[PDB]
Structure formats: structure tokens, C-alpha cells
Image: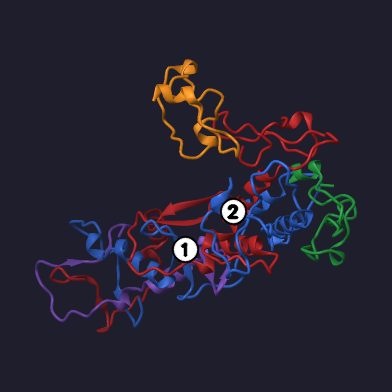
Chain colours: A orange, B red, C blue, D purple, E green
Amino acid sequence: AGIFFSGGLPCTLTVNAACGIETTGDDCPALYYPPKCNVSVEPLQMNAI
Amino acid sequence: AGIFFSGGLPCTLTVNAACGIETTGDDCPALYYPPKCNVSVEPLQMNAIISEIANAINAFGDLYDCSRLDNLKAALQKARSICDLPPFADAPDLDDRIAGCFDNTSSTITVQQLVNLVLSQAGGLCDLPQAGGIGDNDLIAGCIGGAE
Amino acid sequence: AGIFFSGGLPCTLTVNAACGIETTGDDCPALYYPPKCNVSVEPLQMNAIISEIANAINAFGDLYDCSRLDNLKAALQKARSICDLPPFADAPDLDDRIAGCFDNTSSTITVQQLVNLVLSQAGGLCDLPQAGGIGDNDLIAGCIGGAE
Amino acid sequence: GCFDNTSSTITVQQLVNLVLSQAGGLCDLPQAGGIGDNDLIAGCIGGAE
Amino acid sequence: AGIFFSGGLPCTLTVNAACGIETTGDDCPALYYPPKCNVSVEPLQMNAI
């Protein structure tokens, strides 16, 4: 999912996200890391950045 | 999901739940707990309810007081209080609106329509009485030099 | 602690937390359930919230009914609904105030302001039409016989 | 509106009566002394003012 | 039984209970969670709120 985190949450359901992200439909789903307690940043997701 | 059980069910398959709720998009699908014996309230959702009601109480700049029990009721009773609205000094134009009940429907009307409906009932000269005779007190009205 | 779970955490350290809530001192602090997956809601808190909503429903002398899920909705609609306000049983006074949207603001204006604004479109006899002649049988007006 | 410090309503008829009563009448008009040739007299022209 | 807990106790026998609520009748009794040391919230009641 490129720079986004597959399996995350949409921008509404977490903080420090943003709306209005213009994408190519379902192929580019905007997802974000949840505010859950025990999650850590995925390595590969950095590769995109 | 706000104040909905994230993994919940739609209103049709539960009990003591309303139906036909509207939200924004599918990010907020109304859901409730199912009639299971092995489920419990999810604290974060309770936190959402606390946040919502606390915000509601503070709508009109009042101070929440835990020793009370009717803060929301006071807030509601304050909104309906027309007498509490602030005073205003500058004279309004005809387009400035006034609120009243028309056709059993809470709506507003421009002062223009009000002025038209008031002056239109001024009556008419025909209403005036008659003297028949004429005396020196008959100060006849007319456009004397451009000033009535 | 009222509707706030005592022994919780402040808003900054959890989710779904209302921020900047103002209260009557530290004796009514803001605290919320932590994000852990094991904690269980405390019933006595749930007792508090029930009280607030139940009080709100009866803000306008309305009767609760457990068979419907819209009670607060109607008790809120009534507050906004002007059409259901009581009617005054007497005549108004110059000091009586009328609410309006003047200057994009829900404010109050006395009757006298409206009365004076009415005169703007009152007009004078100068506006009346004119004719080249008048029959001996027609009518004239003035301060005749000590009256209009 | 706020009628006698009490939230309530009144029919437009009542306000109309109060406004009309305060409006005034002919006797209120000033008393000019002389008359001129460019003036205009107020009267009823065949049932019309 | 709507929002009110079905098996609770009237206001005077618990804490954080609002006295003198109004209802249609005995079909909708006013009850609250008891201060007992083992009770837990009921979901189906929570749906009501």
C-alpha cells in the first residue's frame, strides 16, 4: 500500500491523520497506524518514505 | 467507532436498539452489542459517551459541578429561555428578521413584511368624523410650502 | 466523582477524551477509563449518566416512556419549537422585548424600537395623488370642530 | 418575545392595535400661518385620498 | 425496561440516583444499579442509552 500502512485505520478513526487524500480508488486505500497500546511501526512501510 | 460498538450488529438483529440512524459515510456504521451472555461494555466507548455529554453540558459556558445531578436539564431549560437573550442597540433595517410562528411553523419574517402588514391597516380618511359646520378652528391640512 | 470515573487518567493520556472541560475546581476533575483491554466499567458511574438523561427528558414536564427510543429527541425539539410557546393573556407594553436575528445575532429589542422603525415607511400626505378639480359634493379633511 | 419577563407569544393583531393607537392623527399636525400659491390641499377626490 | 436497569433498586437505596423521576406508570419503574460489590453493567441496557 505504498507509504500507507495496510491493515491500519482510516484517517477519521485515528489522530494525526488527514482527510482529503486524493487517490486511485480502492487500489490506494488511505490507512493509518491505530492508537492501540502495543503496536510498533512496520519496517517496510518506511521503505516507501 | 464514536459511540457505537465497533464489532457490533445492526439494529435489526439486536434488542432495545433504535433504527434508521444517519451518519457520514460508512466510517460510522451504527452498531450495538448482541444479546450474548459473554460480552461486556467496552470502556473506550463509554469514554466517548462521557465526552459527548460533558461537551453538551458546557455548551453555554456554565461550570460542571459533580455534586449536582441535573446539569443537562438546566442547559436545556436555558436554551428555551427567550428572556435570557442579550439586548441590542443599533436600530435594525427592514431586512433584519424577526422570529414568530406562522402557519404553525417556527420561521422568521423580514421586518419589511411586518411594516407592510402594519401600515396596510392604517385605515383611511373616510373613517374620520364630520363636522358639517365650519369654524375658524378648521386648521385645514395641506402641503404648505412643501412641509405638511 | 459525578459522571467522571475517579481514579482514571487525564484526557491527554487516552482515547475519545474531551479536552479543556471546565469545572468547579479540582473537586470535579476530568478522568477517563484507560486504554487497557481488561478494565471493566463501574456500575455506579452508569447510575450517574442515567440520572442526567432522565432529568433532561423531564426538563419540560414530560413523562418518560420505556417503550420508545426517541424521548430525548422530542424533549429537545420542543425547546426549539416556537409554535408551542404559551400565549400571553394580556396586552403588551413598550418595555416588552422581541427577539430577532439583528446583525446576525439572536438579540432582544424593546417594542419602542420597532414602533419607531415603523414610522420609516409611514409616509405623509405629500405622497397622495392630485386631481385638477373636485366636485362641490366631495369631501375635505382638516382639524375641524376640535377633532380630526 | 419576552412579554412581562415571561416567554410567550401574541397575535399580530394585538401589536397592530398598539402601533396604530400610538401612530397619531391629523390634529397632531403643525399649524401653518399663511397660505401660498404653490401649495396643495389635502382632500378626498371622489372617494380617494 | 428502557434505560433503567431492570432489577435495580429505587433511588433512595443507592448512590448517584436521581430522585422523583416521572414515568407513564408502573410499567416503567425507575430503578438503578445497586451498590453491591459484585454487579456488572448489562449490555442490552447499554444499547438503550
Give how far apart the Cα atoms at labels 1 and 2 are. 14 Å
Residue C98 percent location from the top left of the image: 47, 66
Q: Which quadrant of the figure contains the N terminus of chain C?
A: bottom right
Amino acid at circle 2: Ser
Secondary structure beneath label 1 = strand
Which amino acid does the dot numbered 1 rest on? Ala
Q: Nearer the viewer, residue A28 or C148?
A: A28
Q: Residue B70, how many percent across, how many down? A: 68, 64
Q: Which residue is mark 2?
A: C81
Residue under pointer 1: C99
| Marked residue chain, label 1 | C
Q: Locate residue B94 relative to residue B80 in the image: left or right.
A: left
Q: Is residue D45 left or right of residue B53?
A: left
Most extreme residue toward the top is A27
| Residue D24: image tag | none
Q: Nearer the viewer, residue C60 or C37?
A: C37
| Residue at (48, 56) in percent of width and height | B99
